[PDB]
Image (cartoon, coloured by chain):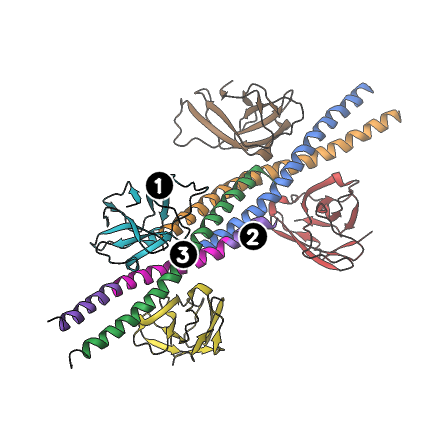
Chain colours: A red, B brown, C cyan, D yellow, E blue, F orange, G green, H purple
Amino acid sequence: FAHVIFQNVAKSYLPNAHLECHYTLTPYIHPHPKDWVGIFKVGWSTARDYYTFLWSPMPEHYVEGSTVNCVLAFQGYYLPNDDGEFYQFCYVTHKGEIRGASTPFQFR
Amino acid sequence: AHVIFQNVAKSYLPNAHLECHYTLTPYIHPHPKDWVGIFKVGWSTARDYYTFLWSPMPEHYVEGSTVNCVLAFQGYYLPNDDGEFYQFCYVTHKGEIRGASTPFQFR
Amino acid sequence: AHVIFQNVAKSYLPNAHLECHYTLTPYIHPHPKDWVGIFKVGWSTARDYYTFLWSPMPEHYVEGSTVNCVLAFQGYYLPNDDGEFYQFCYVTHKGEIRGASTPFQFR
Amino acid sequence: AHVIFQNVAKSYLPNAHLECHYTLTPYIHPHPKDWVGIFKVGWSTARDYYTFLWSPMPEHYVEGSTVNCVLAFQGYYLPNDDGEFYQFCYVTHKGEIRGASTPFQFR
Amino acid sequence: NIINDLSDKLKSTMQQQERDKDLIESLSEDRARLLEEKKKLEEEVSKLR
Amino acid sequence: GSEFKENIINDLSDKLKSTMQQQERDKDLIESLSEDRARLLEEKKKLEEEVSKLRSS
Amino acid sequence: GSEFKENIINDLSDKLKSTMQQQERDKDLIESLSEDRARLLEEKKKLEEEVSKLRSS
Amino acid sequence: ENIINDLSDKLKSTMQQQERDKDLIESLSEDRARLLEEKKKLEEEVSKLRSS
């Protein structure tokens, strides 16, 4: 239930500064063009609780069974404020299930 | 009542660009943090905008002026064909409405 | 002359695009490898062109018809401002000149 | 020669995209209006090129350096299968041929 | 080189424009629904008093 | 350079400035919607609790 | 997608088709010009030979 | 998503080829014109050294 593994997740990111989200599709997930990565405040219940999101691009020339490394760039204006709350990256499939949840971080 | 919206149709195609025409009467002085919002009819406060654009500050403004303006809302700023009524509202940087258009549906 | 050039000016600006207007009279059947060239006045053969463009086959050509055409010469097909006179010429795929305009200068 | 043409074949397919590899020795400083022409063997002056490309100024050039370059001649820049011999030649903006390749044929 | 830089900035600008459009569309509609759910939840709390 | 080239430069530069201007508008909208949507989320959850805590009453 | 995106897509697509259409004209002109210049160059050399071979004959 | 990138990429390439083509056409057509004049000038010096 981590079929998606976020990598190199800092403990904090500078507010309103461009960011890169690194994650790995394990063989156990078949990526879909309506999969997405959200920034979620810690304590989310459902996929509606996202802050902002970006579609996860379909890996080029995908092969079933492969392990695929990905990067999403989050613009500074997609990001929570320096509000003292903790956030995580989450991988949401087109069915709405969360299949990846990173370690928490703060915007500061 | 110090901002007049003009040529407001009773309907607008969803997901199609749109032009909001309004006039600043002498009763108002524009401010860079004035904005024009799309509101569901029946709103209560400025917090109930659907989307908004800042109102571009008229160039070479003279006090006492009467100035015509237009903002372009892209299609992706607009409500869907949801059967509801909306209007344009002019909000000042101080947070007071000063203009409200006739209503329209997105259909 | 089975091909009449139309609206030929006395001069054209160097290095500016250009519209060459011409008419296919009933007397000529257009061939896909006919072409329009710019020629310096005084030319002897079709070999003397400056630059040229293939004349496009009119869509749905009808035997007996009269067909008005336009080719756009880009500025870098054109002679410089060199004090010489030029003309358009229509060259058939056999190599016969069957239309030659009034001359013009590039300036 | 101050320019060295590399990996040039004894022949190239007519009307096939081609790549011309050369090397700027320390002996020359590249200039933006330097150029590489295809010449028919036996040329006399730089006027006898067949076609030509400006040699692209290498970015962040360092004087004394050794810089390798590639230019892509499109098929429609090349001579036909005419039985003749050609070579690449590097011509400086001062008009001097400072590199000249081994000969090839287009066949 | 002027065309290259223009065509790259145009490229990246509109790759971002598409992501922004998708976000604005989701945020717009969901916020609208939240305002109504909030309006109707205060309805239940004041009618429970 | 030529006129053919400059008309496309100008065309490209026009659309670039027009899309970039739209991006500023989009950035300001996104900043407002995302923060206010966050607060509507928390206000909703606080309201749902007083519902459950008053049928608990 | 969007109408904003679709209208820049359509415009850039028309800009692309026009320039490619220009490029086909350019290729045809370069083919004729480069062949003909070559033939002119050999004709000039074959003619200048006949002037020095006529001035000593 | 490819379509934004693909027409930008095709635009870049086809217009960098167009700049080279314009410079060649301008060069080729100017010099071919001068050549045409020199060749006809030569044929006149040839015929008027015979036809006397």
Label 3 packing within 10 angstroms: few (<14), some (14-19), many (20+): many
Q: Amino acid at mark 1?
A: Pro
Side (left or right) of C25 relative to H12: left
Q: Amino acid at mark 2?
A: Asp
What residue would you read off at disc 1? C26
What residue would you read off at disc 2? H6
Position of residue D13 relative to residue A14, above or below, is below
- Circles 2 and 3: CB atoms closer than 8 Å: no
What residue would you read off at disc 3? G26
Q: Secondary structure at mark 3?
A: helix
Residue F30 is drawn in which quadrant? Answer: top right
Position of residue D16 relative to residue C43, above or below, is below
- The percent position of residue G52, horizontal first and vertical second, equals 19, 78
Q: Main secondary structure of the magenta part?
A: helix
Side (left or right) of G56 relative to A22: left
Q: Amino acid at mark 3?
A: Asp
Name the residue rendered at 60%, 35% in the picture.
B76
Residues at discs 2 and 3 both on one chain: no
Q: Secondary structure at mark 1?
A: loop
Name the residue rendered at 49%, 45% in the picture.
G14
Label 1 packing within 10 angstroms: few (<14), some (14-19), many (20+): some
Side (left or right) of B45 relative to B22: right
Q: Nearer the viewer, residue E35 or D65?
A: D65
The answer for which chain carries disc 1 is: C
